[PDB]
Image (cartoon, rainbow over all chains, first blue to last red; front, side, top):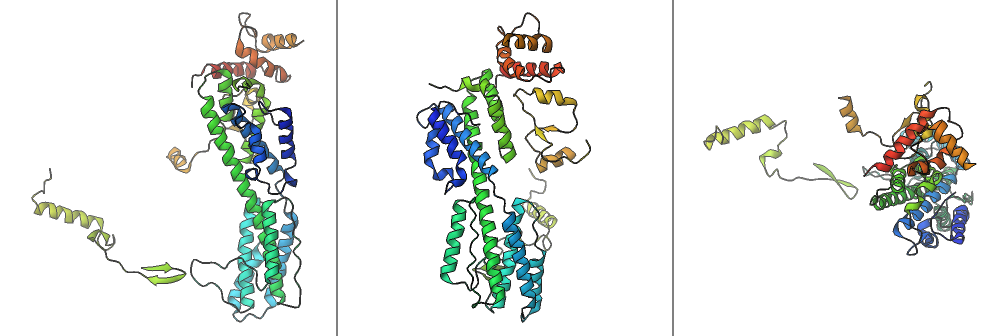
Length: 284
Length: 49
Length: 49
Length: 63
């Protein structure tokens, strides 16, 4: 459990409870919650102590966020089965020039998840590029031939209101990536060919996966940058005094914190022998 | 050269302002060195300072 | 020791921090205590040279 | 007895001479709390001895 310096018990417990409630919190970024950042001791405490408190807050927030790191196995299975559906529908379609059609159907056939978080967003992007090209071929519409360009990841022949609703839902997932709402099933069968319906469902699921992975990575890198900055500043400040407690604290902060595992080890080291270096931090 | 301009390919032609810009295949490095030796000899700097 | 090292066999050295657990495990085989730094590619080639 | 546990560590584990004690030596005084918690690992004494060496080293480093 986190161990701040100089904070009144009410402030510590409300801060801990906010880190506990993180999933329920819409707009889940600390940068969007200045209610929490000044709780560290802004202008109330000394420089070293407020730096230490803010590093503790960022590190604990990173740990809880990494705990809630979303499992997408359900939507990954849905994506794979939808991709199989799109490939199945695509092979029967009477494309005029079957060569490019079968190339894009092959790349749509091959896509499989390799059980690693980072790879799946990029493989999903490739699969959606192929499927959108295939759907645009089916409706005999133009497509990007300029070299260096690539077909955008866009819905084919969906109505304005449904694209608007889907993009607002995706933005809601962007705000809070823990409450998954894949509920956009509203695709009536009278309009559009079956292939375009399948492609629209597939592109929706793929875009949901990509958005959630992108938001996760951006928050992860923000946390790593902030904790690295805090470690740098606090080491620079502790360097000025050569005592056992000060040297011990500098040695603890000396670790690189550019990985989630390294953040865990730094946090656990700071916690376990907190009572050695505490006297270096003034508590007024 | 052939180049890209707002999603089109276009042709671009510009002058080689100096002799150095000829390719190493068509005017290699050793040729430039020997030409410099010739210039130095013309200036009477063949054994240089 | 026997199996390829997973990223959770490898553990970091705590320089300047009290490190009795690692000091007991000096003759151990599996955890392979390592520094946090990793050698860059260029200095890796220099080491090999 | 905290005194008994600290005495056990200092004499049995650390074999420290009677010249040097927890009350006198300050780095020892701060490390004894952490060393008492490790009830095991007591049979291997060179681990604790080396740790005390490097703790006074980190105390004395002017950098």
